[PDB]
Amino acid sequence: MALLEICCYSMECALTAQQNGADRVELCAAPKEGGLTPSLGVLKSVRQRVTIPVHPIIRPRGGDFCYSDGEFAAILEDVRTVRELGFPGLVTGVLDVDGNVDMPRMEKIMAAAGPLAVTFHRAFDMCANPLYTLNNLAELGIARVLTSGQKSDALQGLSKIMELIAHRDAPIIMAGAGVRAENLHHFLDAGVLEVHSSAGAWQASPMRYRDEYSRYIVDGAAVAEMKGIIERHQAK
Amino acid sequence: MALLEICCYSMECALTAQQNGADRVELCAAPKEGGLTPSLGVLKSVRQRVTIPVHPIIRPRGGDFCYSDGEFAAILEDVRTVRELGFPGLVTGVLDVDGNVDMPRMEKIMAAAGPLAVTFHRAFDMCANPLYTLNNLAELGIARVLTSGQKSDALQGLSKIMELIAHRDAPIIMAGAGVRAENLHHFLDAGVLEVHSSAGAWQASPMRYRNEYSRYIVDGAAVAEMKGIIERHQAKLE
Ligand SMILES: [Ca+2]
Image (cartoon, rainbow over all chains, first blue to last red; front, top):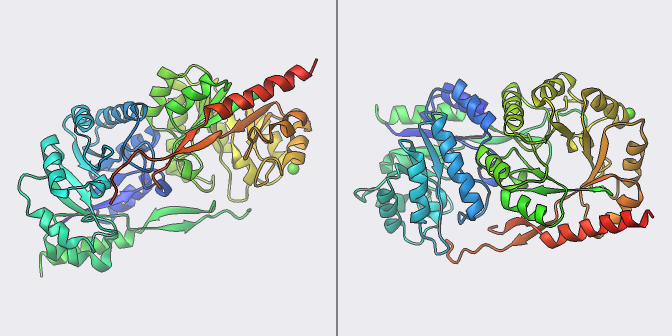
């Protein structure tokens, strides 16, 4: 059956995701930045508490993926860090100014990653040629790619995703961006092998003395609901 | 003369700040979150490339400072790690739901920090009872407090900042929020001994192809300008 990956911004989310049927978790920090590299403290906390596969994101800042040399140095050390801590995979991506995968720098990341399964994130949706990009990711040894079919949301890009899936010798295609219980069946029917969802919402701050009063948390019920949909899909 | 601290979101910013006269750097990640803990890669890079004092922020998420047990576990590990890596200080802060300093949690943070100079950040501006709080921070051994006088910007909170400074030797008061070359004199004349500035600027993305991308960087000239203002102000003192 299809693999369910949940985007998490805390160790507790990863646990809640796990307890509710998630098969994998992408670990990030800074939801308002779209996801940045977690601190060592969070990484260690996850390694001691979460058992399902966790792939931390390696992203020093928001915005584009054309990092400076300084930022890249940090990226390589963070890749080494995640590998040394024992995570089974990681999520990252570097592009050149023309919307192409930065092959030389991605090669250095792959070298540092060693045996870890590397996911190329939505930087993919910013690439000029999706097919040539898939070829490039395969050449690098990338395990999977997170994509919305190069559209605002994965559903709108589902027809493209089905085209991408038919491409031989390519990383696994994981649909992401707007995937939820309500539309999951569309991706399953399309034949998508893996799906990615934040399945979260902003929670109000418990502060009684006073956007600085809200937290981003995962909806465990939504995770459970999606896993259920996946289970029933291959049984009915 | 007053001390100039610059908020940096990268190793390159910190070095640029250092080369332009900054006395100290507060190191963070995620500017859209108001600053979160830097990744280990960034921390290690800074220890290798920057020589002026750098105080990394220890903050797992944006928003309030009433962390969960899980977030707090990470915070203590991050504090221990920053101490291990050799940083001279760090920036953090924890409050309870009523805006009081969470003493048990802060005590644990201080224990983990060892000899590091701990800055209690703008959590102070969200706390209740400023003087009582200053007393508690002194009890904890907090070295300094980053504050806007509990106002939207430090200049508005100038009078409050002065009252904090006058308060029976509380930790060092460092003015922050909207502090820049234009208004620096207000704080220096008020007797503020340490100032914190973003000295921020924006650089367009070099991206030529696209299917928001502006990078938040530091303005070296601005850092130098503020340092010059600080030097001259000190010169005025005979
Ligand atoms: Ca008071």
